Image (tube, rainbow, N blue to C red; front, side):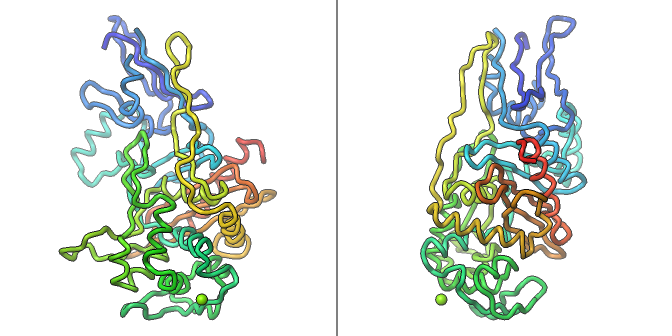
Length: 417
Ligand SMILES: [Mg+2]
């Protein structure tokens, strides 16, 4: 109450939170950037406590004045991510695949950071109001066909199949005594594995899952970070995969997991492992960074530096490897297939004039619609940016269309456009 709490600002210097000395010599917290990165910045209140960065870095911010925290976020990329989600429910994460730095992290619906108290009040009055939910880091989603990046990468790494391997792609087929179906039950005839990735065929990926088997599929997902607790300053639930033991018992569950749908029956007493895959948007961005960065996932980070009131520097982020998902050769082969998705497949809306874009579209099944996903990277040959976006209950392909705008803004900011 008595001393100046430190500021929180973006990497390009937009102040998200600061303390100003009042009339009576007291200090009050100000949030002068409207709804820019609201969920990330969080709030600090003697009534409501803390959340976001205000919570995670409370000790350094509190402090003699407290220390100033500089985030990795770029305000223009952050705004583009928020604009992509405007009027929708969902989330968007933009990362630098070479460092793990988070350039944008947005959730929708959102709110003005300054108005956190009123928003908390509304949440209490209406348990259905989900504005305060951190969807980018804090929520698990079914990734749907975006997860095929993991299945494909695993199949190539383990030599289960190659890009040229041919699979039947019927509209529906029985696997493990129930049905796996292509989107809209489309019959594509025989497809190479590359073509099946371009068209996003569930029946091909289901068969590929059964062929590789539960042990390999689960190990492959774990190589990309599933079932690992990943350290992060904001609450991030562990992304989940079933045990190999559970998937072994149901070829149908295995086939759907390979296609990104978590169909494991968790209503069944006695089930030992979770349904999966279930992932955060951050995790799906990390999957993208593995493909972009020669197979290596860098540790995601949000704080670039901390500086004292003196101006001196007490913390500087050091980009660091988290895990090697696949080999450099495998990553490159997958990246080439994902370029095909955008050039010739379901991802054409992600194309950007003058820069090659590679990525994977996703549809995740819901009762009366779908969640719409895109994970992609640009420039395709040596990416400088990765974007993951989910639009809940979205029109077909909307995730890809919105990702285009976010990627374009990132490339403009970086000078490539
Ligand atoms: Mg074969």
